[PDB]
Length: 126
Ligand SMILES: CCc1ccc(S(N)(=O)=O)cc1
Image 1 (cartoon, rainbow, N blue to C red):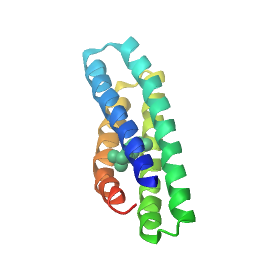
Image 2: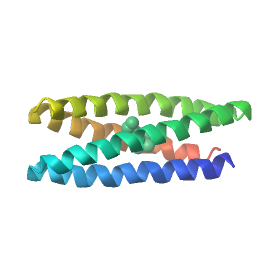
Image 3: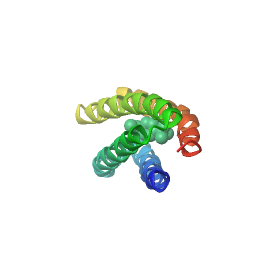
């Protein structure tokens, strides 16, 4: 069902949360080789999560589930804010800018944390 597809998307989101926090620790410890590999893993995970979310929104649309479509539209916009900050973080890392990297890292945390309020409401609506 769309509901079980959302639970799979939720798990993939949780995987990125896990990899993010082991990356933040690696960044703080100065282990740039690790950070590079975690950033590649996160990019893949975010690409997969976006693809599961789009397929869930398209299916809720075909199903006429208006409340779910509203919530998923609001979520996909916030998800894009996260994506943009993530990509900026990656570029900060490429450029050797630890100041901006720290900034984007803290911002992505606040975007992702705020997002979970909606993420939890979508589960209950599908
Ligand atoms: C694209 C980054 C991202 C990943 C996950 C979320 S959330 N916590 O599911 O709203 C928000 C933003």
